[PDB]
Image (tube, coloured by chain):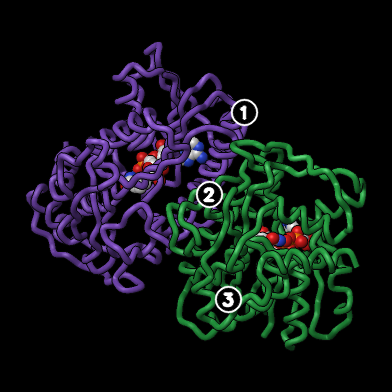
Chain colours: A green, B purple
């Protein structure tokens, strides 16, 4: 199968590229390298089944060229930084809504049969039902990022129905592991490398969120994709997260422990009731019953995934 | 209170303007007259409480000008309802996502405290539960128009939470009445005026939809708005439709009757199972229990609304 991975030079994208290349897919990566790096995929350069295109998906000609002769698109290009929402909403809109719109216009009449989209738990906002099922509603995102992800899902559904392709929408929890350059673990490790004596923690440390290691995440994406390929649904919605959750404070403790440091935790007290920033969801735990029906399950719980990520990042 | 009505020269917007002006609001209209008309609101020019701005919401400067010194925005500007099947994805994206995005960016730098948005039943797609409640999910719109409306809702919710204003999202069923130049009744009347002997009906005539007369619709918008003003919800979702529904064939019969005509009905059979066009939902009936708890209820059922609309249009 011929596949396009947008954002394939990024964190999740490069691990996905690795898996697809190792299973004999013909893989084209489209990435503007605004956050990704060729280093994440450099072992594949020159491989006859691999092609890399450096291009900004704001440019419709580049997107139309990248979808040509492709059977499936894994659309992982985005700016995933929730924190920047109250300073740079334009960036989040452009890199989540606008470029997905461009992709969808390119996909129309292109012979692409499948579109896999990495959405986010943030589409649920402060979800009132926990663990949160895929049919939870009203969907009320509280960040510009979660709103942009939800808007992208909507456009995908409408285009899939109108121009006859199939869409797999995967709402990810927090994904951590090697090659990650955003999120709380990354922030904590680099802060403690700069100053081992103190740790600036945004918010009050009580935010509880489900974490998945990249290995379980890629396994789950492939399991869902293969199940989807064999199914009949035009648009399919799946949560992908862990069975449990962990607090920001516990993450700081694990990071400190693995670095053999004992810093003073400096909690900023946050906003809107201890959130780290405007739009930061306080409680997140996705139901994964639907994903588990495919046979997938995480091998590591949230605490193990955090500890493994820290160890990997310090080596 | 000072309010801005985008699309205020259109069908619903001009009736809303009438009501707000009669209740002593200071009203500003923003409309590019792409589908609306000066005739719908010209009677208010010269009133010291009324201002008209002819401007395209693709223009960020005019939107920024229009939100100045405004307390509430009623955002009714959108793609026209006339033949939505034949409208291109680019037009739908620009007139639903793009101009809403421009509005939200203007609002974050203003004194706007409330944003009311007329969304559409089409965000529900082919809902499996009928009457369809506000918490129906997964939302899987089947047209680019329904997807674009859902994208606008998402952006509104995220901006509301991030930039501290309150949003009232009202999902409208089919709205009919005087000044409407869209939809099946208007098309049927003009077709029978051109040729009284035959009526070409798109689709199979069995599409069943909830119709609300404009008078009930404005009553409901105001009831929900006043209730929302007295509440604390940051973002609130309401359906606004009728208790019942009616088929295209029945509407054609009513139109013929009120015109004293007896034409031959020629059903084209449509597409995708008798739909009038690609992406036309076959069955639509919104649950209005939530709205009815505010004390609102439709005075006219779908049949009465159709009959009154026909009489008004023939005047
Ligand atoms: N990492 C997480 O915890 C997480 C959680 C939920 C969802 N997601 C989603 O998963 C996907 C991957 O995220 P990630 O964490 O690997 O982020 P990342 O930033 O590492 O990867 C995203 C890639 O997109 C590329 N990109 C950005 N804008 C682009 C543009 N205009 N044109 C082309 N390429 C562009 C970047 O260069 C980057 O390589 C995204 O859709 C993200 O929203 C991630
Ligand atoms: N009429 C219905 O049955 C129905 C059903 C569901 C939702 N709605 C929604 O209700 C709202 C009003 O619909 P309506 O039936 O009154 O439609 P309408 O076309 O009569 O009113 C929309 C108005 O917006 C204006 N407009 C469009 N694009 C603009 C732009 N870029 N800048 C400025 N003005 C612009 C048009 O000139 C028009 O006056 C819309 O949001 C529509 O999607 C209507």
Residue picked out by circle 3: A114
Indicate the quadrant where residue B273 lies.
Answer: bottom left
Q: Badge 2 local density, few (<14 within 10 Å), some, or many (20+)?
A: some
Q: Name the spot of residue B247 as percent of width and height, x first.
A: 19, 60
Q: Do labels 2 and 3 share a chain?
A: yes
Q: Residue at 66% across / 71% down in the picture? A: A74
Marks 2/3: CA–CA distance: 30 Å
Is disc 3 placed on a helix, strand or loop? strand
Q: Earlier in the sequence, mark 2 or mark 3?
A: 3
Q: Name the spot of residue B149 as percent of width and height, x first.
A: 46, 50
Camera sees residue B35: no
Q: Are marks 1 and 3 on the same chain?
A: no
Is disc 1 placed on a helix, strand or loop? loop
Chain containing mark 3: A
For the N terminus of chain A, the image quarter is: bottom right
Chain containing mark 2: A
Chain containing mark 1: B
For label 1, being within 8 Å of ligand 2 is answered: no
Q: Residue at 13% across / 45% down in the picture? A: B304
Residue picked out by circle 2: A126
Q: Could you say which is closer to the camera, residue A2 or residue A256?
A: A256
Residue picked out by circle 1: B109
Q: Could you say which is closer to the camera, residue A98 or residue B10?
A: A98
Asked whether, in this view, residue A213 is left or right of residue B195, the answer is right
């Amino acid at each position: 199968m011929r596949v396009l991975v947008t954002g394939g030079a990024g964190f999740i994208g490069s691990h996905l590229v690795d898996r697809l290349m190792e299973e004999g897919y013909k893989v084209r990566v489209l990435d503007d390298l605004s956050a990704g790096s060729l280093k994440n995929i450099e072992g594949w350069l020159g491989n006859e089944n691999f092609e890399f295109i450096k291009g900004d998906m704001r440019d419709v000609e580049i997107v139309s060229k990248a979808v040509k002769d492709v059977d499936a698109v894994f659309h992982l290009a985005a700016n995933p930084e929730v924190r920047i929402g109250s300073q740079s909403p334009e960036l989040l809109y452009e890199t989540n809504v606008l470029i997905t719109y461009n992709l969808l216009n390119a996909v129309r009449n292109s012979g692409v049969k499948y579109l896999v989209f990495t959405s986010s738990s943030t589409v649920y906002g402060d979800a009132k039902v926990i663990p949160t099922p895929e049919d939870y509603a009203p969907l009320e995102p509280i960040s510009v990022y979660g709103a942009a992800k939800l808007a992208a899902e909507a456009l995908i559904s409408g285009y899939a129905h109108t121009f006859d392709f199939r869409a797999l929408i995967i709402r990810l929890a927090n994904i951590i592991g090697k090659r990650s350059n955003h999120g709380v673990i990354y922030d904590f490790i680099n802060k403690l490398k700069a100053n081992p004596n103190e740790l600036e923690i945004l918010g009050d440390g009580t935010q509880r969120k489900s974490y998945l290691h990249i290995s379980d995440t890629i396994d789950g994406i492939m399991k869902l994709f293969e199940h989807f390929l064999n199914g009949e649904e035009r648009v399919d919605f799946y949560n992908l997260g862990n069975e449990d959750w962990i607090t920001v404070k516990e993450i700081a403790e694990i990071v400190s422990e693995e670095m053999n440091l004992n810093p003073r935790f400096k909690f900023t007290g946050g906003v809107d009731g201890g959130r780290g920033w405007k739009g930061d969801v306080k409680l997140m735990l996705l139901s994964i019953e639907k994903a588990k029906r495919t046979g997938w399950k995480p091998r590591m719980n949230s605490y193990e995934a955090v500890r493994k990520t820290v160890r990997e990042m310090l080596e």
